[PDB]
Every structure is written in C-alpha cells, then in structure tokens.
Amino acid sequence: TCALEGGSHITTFDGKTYTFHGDCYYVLAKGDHNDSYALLGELAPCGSTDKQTCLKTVVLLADKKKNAVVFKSDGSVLLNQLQVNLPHVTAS
Amino acid sequence: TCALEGGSHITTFDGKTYTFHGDCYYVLAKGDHNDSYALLGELAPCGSTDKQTCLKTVVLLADKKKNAVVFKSDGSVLLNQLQVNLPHVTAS
Amino acid sequence: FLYNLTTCQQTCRSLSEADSHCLEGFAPVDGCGCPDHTFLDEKGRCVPLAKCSCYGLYLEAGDVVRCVCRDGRLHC
Ligand SMILES: *[C@@H]1O[C@H](CO)[C@@H](O)[C@H](O)[C@H]1NC(C)=O
C-alpha cells in the first residue's frame, strides 16, 4: 500500500515515509511494460505560502491508456471530460 | 443498411423487405468470429391482438460481449443495469 | 453514524445482482449509514426488509408481475 496523506506525506510501498511539497502533476505509479496504467496526482499549493500544499486532482490512465478518469476534489468523477453517474461498473 | 421499421417490417442489408410479427428477443446482427458484437431487439405485441407488434428494447452486446447497453422505449439508456448520462464517449 | 461502512451494505438493487458488484478487498470507512437491518430504499430513509423495493426500474412493494414484490427476493 502506497499512501499520499496530508498535502505532502508520501509513504512508499516499502515503508519509506517522506515529505515533498510540490507544484505540478506527478507520476505516482505506472506500469513498466508499454501501456498498462499510469496514476497521476496534482500536488499544488492550496494555502498562502509554497509550503502549504494540497492534493487536488487524481488522474487515472487505464485500459491501454485510452481511458482517462479524473477525480476532482468536490466529488465530480468524470470520464473523458464528461460527467458520469455513480456506480459505474465496466469490464476492466 | 438494415432497417427495422414499424412494429414489424425488416429490410435486410441486400434489399429483401419482409413482415414478421414476433414475440421474443431476436438476434438482429452478430459477428461470426467468436465475440465481436451482437445486436438484439424485442418485437413483442403492443396492442390488443398478436398481429399488433412493436419494437420495445434494443440490446447491444459489445466489447467482447462484456458490456451490455440497453435502449428502452422511453429514452433511459442504461449500461450494465445502471443509468448513464448522455453523451457518453469511450475508447471503443 | 457508523465506523464500519462497506460497499456491500447497499440497497436492494444491489441484492438484484448480488454477485456482480461487491468488490471484496477494501477497508471499511466511517460515514452515515443504516444499522444491522433495514436496508436502504431508493431514496430517503431506509425502510425494513419487508417493504424495501423490487428492482429495469425499482418498483414499489405493491406490484405483481407472476412475481409478487416481496422482501428482497422475487418469487419468479
Ligand atoms: C458494525 O459494528 C457494529 C457493532 O456495534 C455492528 O452493527 C456490526 O458488527 C457492524 N455493522 C454492519 C456490518 O453493518
């Protein structure tokens, strides 16, 4: 289990907790082969200074990287820039 | 173009118009290989007698037959027994 | 307010599939939910098991197909 807690506290799959405070989209986990998946995540400043950062958007690029799923920080799950209704059960 | 007009007037891909008046789910078109797709359609009686039939439900079994899409006769497009919001653009 | 809310404590529409979407392997979370019985209805409060729903559109507990709408399962 990899965890991304607080604004900036990454705990890797092998222990190893560390603090980062970024401002970009970052690759959190991706499969190495050519395609499999890629999990992104926005770690941008939410408060006043640059040291007050927050997670804002989780992006999942699945199914041979042709389906993009976006998890905004107000609910609002949207598939390929279009709102979806939950639950949403598919084949993969 | 294959057309299914009225309650019961099938026009095949090669001309050949005919009248049927069924009461079941029927296979309208399906791919021959092992999977590709299958398009069903309900032709059930809607009026009083059995000769007053209507189209009621179009069922599409796509993406290696793991995704079922249902077109009821009041709008109400639903994917895998769950309502969807339109438009709904995917990879396939 | 619960401390052990899980995916498969859902409505009787989840009982219509009952093997399609349960997804074991996650962790329980804490939110608003119903107690050990009286499963969730289509909207609003959670009525008991006898007059839950019959899920197609979720029909009320007075409809006869020949399947009388009953507690969770249908006599089909
Ligand atoms: C959660 O724990 C309580 C114990 O107070 C009990 O209702 C039951 O074990 C759990 N509830 C569920 C699984 O709905």
Image (tube, coloured by chain):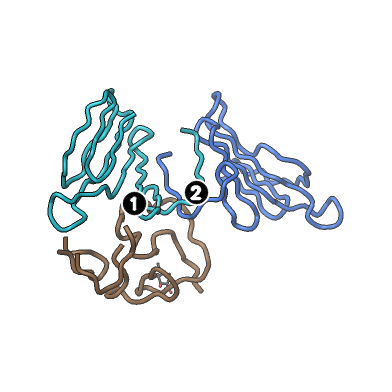
Chain colours: A blue, B cyan, C brown
Percent from the top left, x then y, of residue B60?
A: 33, 40
Percent from the top left, x then y, of residue C36?
A: 37, 73
Alpha carbons under labels 1 and 2: distance apart:
14 Å
Residue at 36% in and 76% down? C47
Q: Residues within 10 Å of mark 2 (few under 14, many from 20)?
A: few
Q: Is residue C21 left or right of residue C63?
A: right
Label 2 CB less than 8 angstroms from ligand 1: no
Residue at 31% in and 43% down? B59
Percent from the top left, x then y, of residue C26?
A: 47, 53
Residue at 40% in and 53% down? B75
Residue located beneath label 2 in the image: B86
Residue at 32% in and 72% down? C52
Q: Is residue B6 left or right of residue B83?
A: left
* Image quadrant in which you'd find residue B19: top left
Label 1 CB less than 8 angstroms from ligand 1: no
Does dot 2 land on a helix, a strand or a loop? loop
Residue located beneath label 1 in the image: B72
Of the pair B77 and A71, the residue shown nearer to us: B77
Does dot 1 land on a helix, a strand or a loop? strand
Image quarter for ligand 1 equals bottom left
Which of the labelled discs sits on residue C14, or is there none?
Answer: none
